[PDB]
Image (tube, coloured by chain):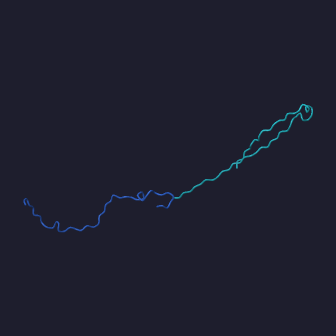
Chain colours: A cyan, B blue
Amino acid sequence: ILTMLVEPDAGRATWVAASAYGSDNTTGSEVTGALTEIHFSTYKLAAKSFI
Amino acid sequence: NQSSSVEVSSESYETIFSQRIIRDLQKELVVGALFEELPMSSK
């Protein structure tokens, strides 16, 4: 196997209200993401002959 | 041959043709040339 890393999709920000300009919500929201993987393999092809 | 994996087209390519011609025993000739010859110059 040969395994590679796949970047995730997109997140998004939040529109904070005017009230939270001094409160803790001024920072907005937390955005997370997780990576993923892909795998590859091979197959065998063969033939024989006689003389 | 028709025994291995690959085969020839036909027996013509499995054969060698020779230009040698041979003959059996032939009867010997005896009376043809045992008498004397009498040449002629007329009928």
Q: Quadrant of residue B42?
A: bottom left
- Give how far across and how far down residue A19 sits, in percent: 91, 32
Q: Residue at x 44, y 56 (%)?
A: B9
- Side (left or right) of B33 relative to A47: left
Foreground pick, B38 / B8 = B8
Q: Nearer the viewer, residue B38 or B14?
A: B14
Query: How many dots with numbers?
Result: 0
Q: Nearer the viewer, residue B7 or A17?
A: A17
Residue B40 is situated, as x and y percent measured from the top left of the image, at 8, 61
Query: Where on the picture, by quarter, is residue A29?
Result: top right
Please name the residue shown 17% across and 68% down the image: B31
Q: Position of residue B24 (x, y in %)?
A: 29, 66
Q: Is residue B31 above or below residue A20?
A: below
Residue sitting nearer the eye, A31 or A44: A31
Q: Which residue is drawn at the image coordinates 78% and 38% (left, top)?
A: A10
- In x, y percent, where is residue A26? 89, 33
Please determine whether, in this image, residue A10 is positioned above or below residue B23. above
In the displayed structure image, the side of residue A4 where residue B25 appears, left or right = left
The residue under the point 13% across, 67% down is B35
Q: Examine the rendered structure and indicate whether residue A15 appears above or below residue B10.
A: above
